[PDB]
Amino acid sequence: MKSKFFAQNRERLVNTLPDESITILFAGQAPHMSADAHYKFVPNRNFYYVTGIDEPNVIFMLKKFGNSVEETLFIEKSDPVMEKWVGKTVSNEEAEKISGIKKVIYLDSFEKTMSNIFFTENVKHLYLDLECREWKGTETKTLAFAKHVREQYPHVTIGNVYPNICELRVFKTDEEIEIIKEAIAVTKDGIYNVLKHAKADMMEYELEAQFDFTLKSSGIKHHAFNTILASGKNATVLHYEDNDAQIQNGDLVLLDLGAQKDYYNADISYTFPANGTFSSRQKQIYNIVLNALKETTEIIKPGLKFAALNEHAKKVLAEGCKAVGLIQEDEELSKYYYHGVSHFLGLDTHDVGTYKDRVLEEGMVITIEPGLYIEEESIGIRIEDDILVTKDGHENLSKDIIREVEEIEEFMRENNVNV
Amino acid sequence: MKSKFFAQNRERLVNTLPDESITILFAGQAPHMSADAHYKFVPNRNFYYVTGIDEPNVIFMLKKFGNSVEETLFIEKSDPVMEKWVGKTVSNEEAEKISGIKKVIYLDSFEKTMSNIFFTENVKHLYLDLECREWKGTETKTLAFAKHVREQYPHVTIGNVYPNICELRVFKTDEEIEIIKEAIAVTKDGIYNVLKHAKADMMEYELEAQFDFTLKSSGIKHHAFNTILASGKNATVLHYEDNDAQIQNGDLVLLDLGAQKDYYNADISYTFPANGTFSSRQKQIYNIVLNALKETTEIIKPGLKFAALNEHAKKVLAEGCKAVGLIQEDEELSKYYYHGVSHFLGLDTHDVGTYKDRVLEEGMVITIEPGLYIEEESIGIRIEDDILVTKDGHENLSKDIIREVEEIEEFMRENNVNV
Amino acid sequence: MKSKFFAQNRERLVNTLPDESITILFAGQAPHMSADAHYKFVPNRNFYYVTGIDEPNVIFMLKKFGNSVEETLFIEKSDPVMEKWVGKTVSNEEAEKISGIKKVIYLDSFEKTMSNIFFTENVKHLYLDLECREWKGTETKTLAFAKHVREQYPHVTIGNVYPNICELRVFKTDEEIEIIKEAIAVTKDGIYNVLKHAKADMMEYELEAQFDFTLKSSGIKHHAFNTILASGKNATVLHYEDNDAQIQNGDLVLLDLGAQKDYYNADISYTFPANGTFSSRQKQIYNIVLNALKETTEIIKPGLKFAALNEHAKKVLAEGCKAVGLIQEDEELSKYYYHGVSHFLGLDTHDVGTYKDRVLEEGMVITIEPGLYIEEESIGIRIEDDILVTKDGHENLSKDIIREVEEIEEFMRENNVNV
Amino acid sequence: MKSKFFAQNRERLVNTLPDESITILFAGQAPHMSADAHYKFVPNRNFYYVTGIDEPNVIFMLKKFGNSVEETLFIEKSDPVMEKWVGKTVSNEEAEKISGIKKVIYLDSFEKTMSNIFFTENVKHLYLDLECREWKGTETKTLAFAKHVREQYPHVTIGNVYPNICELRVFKTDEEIEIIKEAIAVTKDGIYNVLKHAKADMMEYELEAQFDFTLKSSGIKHHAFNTILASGKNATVLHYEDNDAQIQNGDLVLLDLGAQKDYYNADISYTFPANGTFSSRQKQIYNIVLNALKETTEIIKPGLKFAALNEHAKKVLAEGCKAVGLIQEDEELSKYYYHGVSHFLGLDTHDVGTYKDRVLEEGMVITIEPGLYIEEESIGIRIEDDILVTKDGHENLSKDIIREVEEIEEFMRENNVNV
Ligand SMILES: [Mn+2]
Ligand SMILES: [Mn+2]
Ligand SMILES: [Mn+2]
Ligand SMILES: [Mn+2]
Ligand SMILES: [Mn+2]
Ligand SMILES: [Mn+2]
Ligand SMILES: [Mn+2]
Ligand SMILES: [Mn+2]
């Protein structure tokens, strides 16, 4: 991932913003976890998308005046003492090389800069990234910053740049797609490794261990999200994360997981039989889902209404359910299939972007993940691919992952130590 | 960990609080990570220590009036929709069973309870757990709550119960020490597994993968802290976490890691030769550090001033450094050893409790971690044990971990595939 | 009053609001009175006019997006315990039937809806009913709400819908006029009852009781405002409410009062001799006022500047005063007549709507209430009618109430038990 | 009520407050009702009890320093314009005469007095009347005042004087009791008036009108609380206020109402048969309730725990219910009797004062109000007397009200036009 990518993102962002306005983005800090410990730092995707900087506590500013456009970074100064504890923070020159932003100055001059901007330069329009997902959320640095601006500069108009950046993230470039592909690749390897080691009478976490191992030893530092490794009746809980039950012989195992490469996410659901063999009933239910996957993936092309995806998924899932006698009428389905089939994928696993009235266009990456959940039969199945919308159709980024009942049983037979 | 342990914690806590006072503790929730994702929930250690409840969103209350003492829990009501996404939350009866608290009610009655406590019952003294580590920190649910109490009940005196509970956590019971013991035990297995798989020309993270595997397969859901796996020059950064450099032949490998069992933490530092053989120079520096370990461990017993540990450590390290020729005078040491030698250990890896004027006493668990860091030689060494203070001395909780140069070289010969 | 009425109110309201905006109205709750008691709940007239709902604590919401328009109500869930104290609150179905609003959901989902509205749907323009009559007023739930919106969604623009709804309330429909007519009708009955029971040497409140009785026994739950029942010198205080003096023989009695029907208000002032016979002097002053009432009512018609009413009232009052000898020049009138002659009438007694530059138009209901107040003679007289502005003139909604000196003396002779 | 009464109230209050402290009480103002209308002003009882001033917008201040004690009143200055609308506000001399407070100054000097108090005199301890009954209540003038003091004078300790005054109000003097007696007297007259006019096939409000009439024409300006006039099944809803149903022949009618004299409250519940005859079944239930009344009133005397009243009430209601076969065991009572039997009475209807661990003492006025409510039989009966606790027993303040079934049937036969 090279500076040119980020520079172009800024060009595009610039074109969405009014003239005579300033925009500020904050890298953020890792939140407190417990005692003196903090959580692992997670780069703010919008900030990162715009600056290419993956470190805390940097600040980015974009001034738009007349025909001019001025971008600036504020980084930390070096601290010889802290370097013996945590290593060196990004340097002036590194920051410029990475971000492609020419003007890189220090945080200690941010306050004075604020003073000039809002007084000397009579700026009237400020944009911040105002992501606020909860009505009763608690105050964040950003919101606090907005409150401050409101009090010192009550005449300044505040706008939200969040939506502006999200709508750009919706359309992936080729190098973005390449990284996702790599993430998927490693996820496949992880899954295959699970398939090669799975057996009955084995703890769910013993299997999770194998997936984690494959990712870790290939250099992947993070997962896309928390691994779902659910066997038997547990696969009925959508985001089951306990992963601490014993896998019974005859149990189906649902995997929902993904590696993360350079801050891009893969997202795969995969269901297989623990003992290497699908039961007659499991084979039925699995193929109904798998149909819904193929059918739904099929209709993907520019011009299609996003809402059509789940509509079709529900149609196909209902036909399969009837055929098999699980239900009589379409309405009963919500008892066995109670989520949406698709979501954007990118810098975030449930990537950003509006869905309302969304129409599919070239460049979008979305997931397709139909599933069926039968509590009384202790069967949970979900199968999920990551699809790229192309110029005149789609490309299945995760097609290399074998999905057919025959292919799975065969693979576990050749490769699984204890089958 | 059985409810009697938490009931007793509450009994001791009660004795530290004034009469005519109410205390409230909050379980909290997982902080925002990115987009719709949150971090993994980490039980608030104080809240956990007092209630034994490891779920979010619960509230605890302790009324102390006259001769009375009334404990209450507020839990979430069940939600048939969310149960299909995340599973059931603790039930009315389970909470009672776990915490030993008799009166358990629901959150939707918390507000009305507030109104009565502060109006009808004329309560004037409220205690909150006010952990505030940063002067320019951002507002938290608790601080917000205090603010609200200040505005609605200005006459109510607010006190901080944080210090009360930390001082209790300083003294571990037998059942506490048993869990720490288990945590160390797995850590050991982890380390051994690293020792048996290590070789030259191998990625740091490849070795981390092996440690992670051992823990995960044994059911351990979390680490104590972010594993440090630093080779050659990298061992010189105290909290080096990149774990993404190649291990050179002749390199030394510094491990600083620990498993966590039922929320209690192990914390071990271990240093070994990648190729299974210490070089002369390395053997020297190692033993110097080893000595400091045994020496400083030696003097541990109730009555000893905490400050004394680091004094002795510095003294013994300096002597080793002189004899070897690394330094001339004691003052130069700080160039090669620039941290404390000890810290409390417990529900937090850097456990709670004041250090100022601290004297050791039966019941404390602490670490001893002398090290030497020689930048110009690309040598970093740290050796760390978890010591328990007994009634007339100490007990080294991690004595089973082999430390001698001979023991290590011998072990890697017998067990390491590629030596 | 049927749902079509309110439905049309909302259609009109919609046409005054910009596109891409949301509007929220709160029913409110009764204010604290003393100890655990609250005042009688008074439906917020704007909220009522829009929803047709007379209960507390409901919330109304109107989204205007693209060509779409979505109306939603939030109501209280039923509570089997409270139903034993206060009775059932409006039900899901009743609310729909009354308001004509199809979507009716519960308050416990209001917060989540807020989150979605202001995050997911990127709403930028919010309208609230911001009636704020006092510069140093105290914070209200609505202002507290705006403050919250401002802190969480600093980019959101806040508009005031109060003016929008008031201007709609200014033009009454036929159904509205009818209700006003009913309210006036009862007021008449109440007045006649007073006339038939009045005598000298009687407590002002004794007469009040007779008027209250007529209204209550006729089903009327509330008065328009606080009954004014002023005898002798007391009629000189414009809003005299004590109502606790003894009516002297020879005293005139000024009645200012009005029944309220279905939340619409009547408003009538009526003066008469306690002993059933006007004195010469009283006949003079009464006729001066009655002249102003007729003359000022006479000029009412679409096109007329509202400011003209009081100009003419003054003119005519001064004419009567000159003729009788009370004053020499027009300027002296302010000593005897010191209020406006007219105000709007409707869901509020001093109904809403601007007066600056106002021109009369069909549909408006206004009052005409000239008076004279002569302190040194202990005479205070006011006669007030409720006028409807019609297509080409006016209609006196209270013409049935007899006003002539001879008509009153005669009525009291025939009907007053002690004359 | 003469000034000496309020003067003694302040003397007692003074003895409950620490030395070196200042106390401020606010008269308040009438809250906004609708548009330009405000609710009727209701003197804040604590303020009233301390000052004897029933006007709004006054401020009272008590300085306690060394051996000194300085009381001050701040009143409004006269406004010649407003006097023509609302009348004269309390004058400098009237204020002194009414309150017994010697130093009376004007509001326009309140602010400067605040400065001197909190700067020049170094006052550290401030008491306010901090009644706050709702955890999520809205900011009040007093809370805003507190907040202000907190911002300008952060060192100043704020205490709540509410409890202090409430405990004084709990013990009534002889002149207080007299007034309550008067309120009760009128209430009785009003009830009898209702008995004399009640018949079947008559609107509930038609009866309420009769009760209001008696009160109004006797000079009573306010009701204790909202008249409850519940017939048939409606008597089942404890605070039924609609009062708009038709009384069916055979219906029992439940009155719960009370006159207010000079701010003191009566509170009576009276049940009778609409047609003048108790049915067998009604006679049964009525007598059970009336027993509970006599029995519970009986045990009242200094030394008796307040909690005993309800315990005995339940005990005696159960016996009656068993005897009649309405229930089998005591537990079933909650189905038909679901409230407390007693509450303090005074300047408030549910008068102030703590109940927890309360022991009855001479001077206390409390109500006794057993009831039975049978939904399936459409029968709701409550009977309530106001009791005074005397030196060695109790005095029934409302004994003159006839309660026996024969007494009532007789009274209605004698006096009721239509029986
Ligand atoms: Mn997934
Ligand atoms: Mn997914
Ligand atoms: Mn360590
Ligand atoms: Mn350590
Ligand atoms: Mn009027
Ligand atoms: Mn008027
Ligand atoms: Mn009552
Ligand atoms: Mn009562």
Image (cartoon, coloured by chain):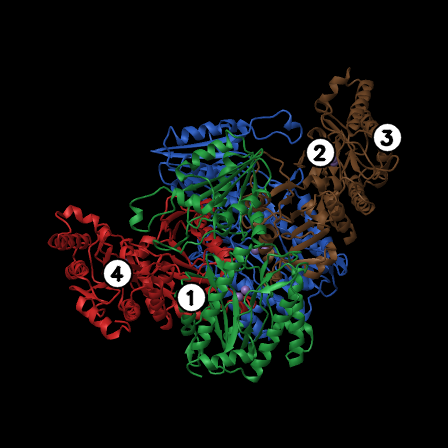
Chain colours: A green, B red, C brown, D blue
| Residue that carries the numbered disc 3 in the rendered image | C298
**First in residue order: circle 2 vs circle 3:** 2
- Residue with the mark numbered 4: B251
Report if the CB atoms under discs 2 and 4 are less than 8 Å apart: no
- Between the C-alphas of marks 1 and 2, the distance is 91 Å
For discs 1 and 3, the disc positioned in front in the rendered view: 1
Q: Does the residue labelled 1 lie within 8 Å of ligand 1?
A: no
Give the CA distance from mark 2 to mark 4: 105 Å
Q: How many residues crowd around disc 1 within 10 Å: few (fewer than 14), some, or many (20 or more)?
A: many
Q: Is A34 placed left or right of B112 in the picture?
A: left
Residue A215 is labelled as 1
- Total labels: the figure holds 4
Kindly identify the amino acid type of the residue bearing the numbered disc 1.
Answer: Leu
Secondary structure, mark 2, is: strand
Q: Check disc 4: other Cα within 10 Å, few if <14, some if 14-19, many if 20+.
A: many
Chain ID at mark 3: C
Assign a secondary structure to mark 3: helix
How far apart, in angstroms, are the residues tagged by discs 1 and 4? Answer: 25 Å
Query: Residue D267 in the image: x percent, y percent?
Result: 58, 53
Q: Which amino acid does label 3 sit on?
A: Glu
CA distance for labels 4 and 3: 108 Å
